Length: 33
Image 1 (spheres, rainbow, N blue to C red):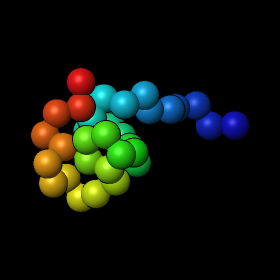
Image 2: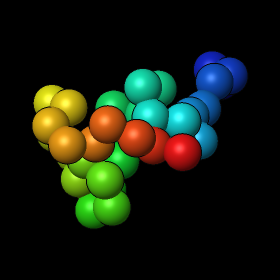
Image 3: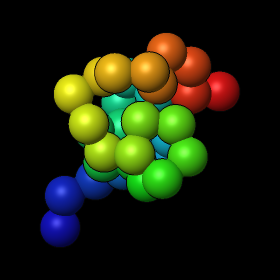
């Protein structure tokens, strides 16, 4: 239907899991890589 999916750049992944930000309003996840 709609094209467009994030991979895990950092500023483009508002979801993310337990690894850096762990789903939060930018706290310590100052680096995605």
